[PDB]
Each structure stands twice: as C-alpha cells, then as structure tokens.
Length: 464
Ligand SMILES: [Ca+2]
Image (cartoon, rainbow, N blue to C red):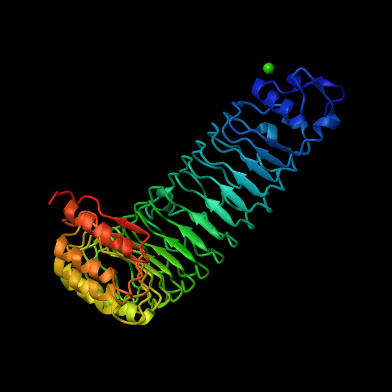
C-alpha cells in the first residue's frame, strides 16, 4: 500500500514497466503521481514485448486479474507472489531459468498459466499444489528434464497440459534410476495432452492409466520404436491420437482396441513395415487414418474392414503391393464413406490402378479425391481410369503428376472428361511425358468441361 501521491517512476524502478503503468492508467508521464485508489483500479495489464526486466512495484496492485507479460526479460517473479486475484497469466518468452517451490502458493484463482518458451530445467515438488481452479498449463519450449512423481499434484481441474519441446525422455526409461517417473498420476480431468518433441524412446505402460477424460494425446516427434500393449488400455474417451514422426517399427496387436471413439489416428512418418490384423478392428468411429511415409508393402485381408466410417485414408510414400490395392478397393465397395484416398509415391502400376478402377466402377463409391502421383502408371492404366471418369460421378479431384502417361494416355482422359458423367473439378497432369502441343490441345478441349475449376500441366516441355 501507498499513502501519498507518488510518482510511478518511484514505485516501478524498471523504466520500461513504469511506462507500462503510466500507459495503463492513461497518464502523460512516469513523473505523474498516482494514488492507491488509482493503483486499485487496475484489473488488467497487457505488456507483451515491452522490454521489461523487472515487475517490482506490481506488489502494490492488489486487483490484477489478467496479466500478460509475454516477450520480456523477466528472470524473477517474486513481485507476483501475493496478487491473489490473478486468473490469467502469461509469462511466455521471458528469461526464467528456475522457479521456487511455492511462488504460486498464493495464486488460488489462477485458471490459465502460460510458462512456454522459457529455460526451465526442472520443477520442484508441488510447485502448483494450490492451483485447484487451474485448467490450462503451458510449459512447452522449455529445457525440462527433472520432474518427480508429484510435480503436478493438486492440479485436479486441469483440462489442457502442454509439455512439448522439452527434454523429459530419460524420466520415462525403465532403467532410469528409481524406475520411470509417473508424473501424470491423478490427472483425471485432463482432456488435452501434448508430449511431442521430447526425445522419448520408451513409453511405460501405465503412464496414462489415470487419464479417464483424455480426448487428445499428442506423442508426435519423439524417438519411439514400440508401444507396450495396453499403454492406451484405459484412454476410453480418446478422439485424437497423434503418433506421427517416431521410429515405430512394430505395433502390438490391440494397442488401440479400447479406443472406440477415436476419430483420427496419425501414424505417419515412421518405419512400419507391417500391421497386425485386428489392429483397427474396434475403431468404428475412425474417420481419418494417415499412414504416409512408412515402409508398408503387404497387409492382412480386413486390416481396413471394420473402418466403415473411414473418410480419408493416406498411404502416400509407401511400397504398397497390388494385393493391398484390392483390399482398399474392397473397402470402398462396402464402406461407401471413403472420400479422400492418397496413394502417392507407391508402385501401383496398371495392376493396381485396375484394382482401383473396380471400386470406382461400383455405384456406391463416394470417392471424391484420388491421388496417384508417381505411381508408375502407364498409358494403358489410363484406358482403365478413363472408364471410371465417365461414370464415377462423385469423383472431383484426380492427381496423376509425375507419371509416364504420354499423349495417348492423356487423350484417353480428355475423351473421358468431355463425357456427360464427368463431374471432375481438378486434374493434375504435371510431368506426365507431354509436349506443349499436347498441353495446349488439352487445355483447349477442357474449357468445355463443365465442372473443371483447376488444371495443371507443368513439367511437360517439348515443342512438337
Ligand atoms: Ca528507473
């Protein structure tokens, strides 16, 4: 408390923060005197990127609720201890290396706490004990490596917790001294967990066993090579699972068997070379499966069977076998939901494209986008595709870039696309072995194509 009109300057030693208080109170100068009543009138401060090193003085602002200090140079935050009305707090992008146990002992009304992009290395026990109303905690982009069992104890109303771009990996290795640290114990309301970008190479079963309420788990960009059976056993409410960008080489059978609400599974960028049958048996809600950038070849009949709600399937960048193309096509004759199908950079060839035309020729195909970039397709894969382009009325996008289509192949497609049942909006035929003469004839005849918004003919550079 102050009891005399005092210059801002005298209360807030940091020239930059004084200027913040001046602005915040609408005074012309830091030399202007303030009263306690005026300091009591401050319930919100927005001071991101203000070149602040020091919030000394803020102690005298008993009523602050919303405090935004992102982008400054704060290392200490003692001055905040007792601002008990704080509900929203942004301290991201400062120079905080360390936090005392108990700095938030008194911040009982805090609901949102952003601590991202600092240089925290560890956190003492119960550093958030008394934040019972806290629902969002962001600790991404720190250097965190050292947490105990109970660093997140007391946080029983937490709904979002972001730990991305830290270095927690060693804490979850089995040989780690004491065993792995199960620091998600009790987090019963947690709905959103982002654990991407640590160096995680093991994942103990039971790290998530209490997360009854989880909807989104992000494990992207770690070093994982396998998942223990039942590491998701009790994540029953889960809708989004992101396992992209790991080293996954095998999945156990029924790692996801208890995840019936799952709508989105990102398995992209790994080294999966196989998938056990049944792995997708109980995912009847799943609408997006992304398996791109992996080393797939063969797959059991009915790895995709139960996925009758599936809507986008991405198998780009694999070495899919002609067999697998028949399963996919199989799915489409039955599912009648699959809309996007990405098969880029696979050796499909005529053999696969024919298999895939079978479905497209089936009245019940809902397929809207097909991408067969660089699929090693021929001019006679196009006789077969053309067949469908006349019929498959739901088909709107077709990408055949970087294939050896040639002119006789392209012509097939123009006679098809000029046909009454063509509803195609987009055609990509870049690098398909075409002349300008070709490309110009193509462009011209497709101006008559009623549905065609979009047409690419690049990397086809020969004049006659
Ligand atoms: Ca000063």
